[PDB]
Image (cartoon, rainbow over all chains, first blue to last red; front, top):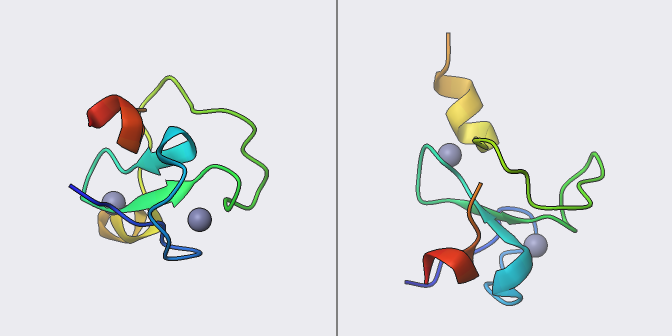
Length: 54
Length: 8
Ligand SMILES: [Zn+2]
Ligand SMILES: [Zn+2]
């Protein structure tokens, strides 16, 4: 299905569009600040998921 | 981490 980026709200450029390992949210690596130059190989959690951690 | 492309 069509996930969208939390920052820019577009679902284009699938190749750069990170999925959150904890929910159905997404972010383009090029929209991320700080600079994310590549798709990380480990788990990645969006900011909404960080809010639920302890 | 997986992308929208690697998941679809
Ligand atoms: Zn974006
Ligand atoms: Zn999340």
